[PDB]
Amino acid sequence: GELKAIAQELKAIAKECKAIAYELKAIAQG
Amino acid sequence: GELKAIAQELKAIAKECKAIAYELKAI
Amino acid sequence: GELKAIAQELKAIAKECKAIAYELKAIAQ
Amino acid sequence: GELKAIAQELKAIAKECKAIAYELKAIAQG
Amino acid sequence: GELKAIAQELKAIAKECKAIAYELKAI
Amino acid sequence: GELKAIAQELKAIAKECKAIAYELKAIAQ
């Protein structure tokens, strides 16, 4: 269904935001 | 339908966030 | 309708995230 | 209504993402 | 209700994006 | 339900944005 589809794309956005934080943590460490 | 339209725009946001993470690796 | 309004604001968010990616590439050079 | 409330918070998120791009543009310019 | 719950989490995301923009000024 | 699932993923996004803000403050030092 369509609401499940929306939840799955939000899950994808959360994964990429976690990736952004991960790369920034590396930048913070030099 | 409009709910599918919403899912498609969320897909676009996820793609751009992926791009942001990738560009940060070049910093 | 309201659901169309939600899709249009999501389109706006995707556009700004694309701008963010563009500027980060400029910073990395 | 509740769907209008959701649209208004998305509008707020878009404004802040525009702000993020604006500050990054300044960083890119030194 | 659940739609109000969704609006409240969106409010939280907007607050954090505002914080991100502010921290970038210190860079 | 599905609407609760959507709220929970939004909560996850807000948590990651908070992590992003934390790391940017660390970078600025």
Image (cartoon, coloured by chain):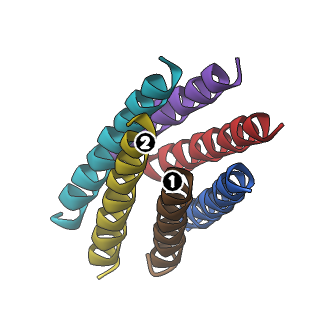
Chain colours: A blue, B brown, C yellow, D cyan, E purple, F red
Q: Which quadrant holds the C terminus of chain B?
A: bottom left
Q: Is residue F18 above or below residue D30?
A: above
Q: Residue at x 32, y 61 (%)?
A: C15
Q: Which residue type does callout 2 highlight?
A: Ile
Residue E19 screen position, x and y as percent: 44, 35
Q: How many marks?
A: 2
Image side of residue B2 versus residue D11, left or right: right
CB under 8 Å between discs 2 and 1: yes
Which residue in the structure is indicated by mark 2?
A: C6
Residue B22 screen position, x and y as percent: 52, 78
Q: Secondary structure at mark 1?
A: helix
Residue E2 screen position, x and y as percent: 70, 24
Between F25 and B18, the one lying in front of the other is B18
- Answer whether residue E27 is visible to the viewer in this image: no
Between F10 and C11, the one lying in front of the other is C11
Q: On what subunit does the disc labeled 2 rest?
A: C
Q: Residue at x 36, y 45 (%)?
A: C9
Q: Is residue A9 above or below residue B22?
A: above
Image side of residue C18 versus residue B15, left or right: left
Residue extending furthest toward the front: B1
Q: Is residue F7 above or below residue B23?
A: above
- Tell me the CA gap for discs 2 and 1: 7 Å
* Circle 1 residues within 10 Å: few <14, some 14–19, many ≥20: many
Which residue in the structure is indicated by mark 1?
A: B6
Q: Residue at x 49, y 43 (%)?
A: F25
Q: Which residue type does callout 1 highlight?
A: Ile
Q: On what subunit does the disc labeled 1 rest?
A: B
Image side of residue E1 versus residue E20, left or right: right
- Answer whether residue F24 is visible to the viewer in this image: yes
* Circle 2 residues within 10 Å: few <14, some 14–19, many ≥20: many
Residue C2 screen position, x and y as percent: 41, 34
Q: Secondary structure at mark 2?
A: helix
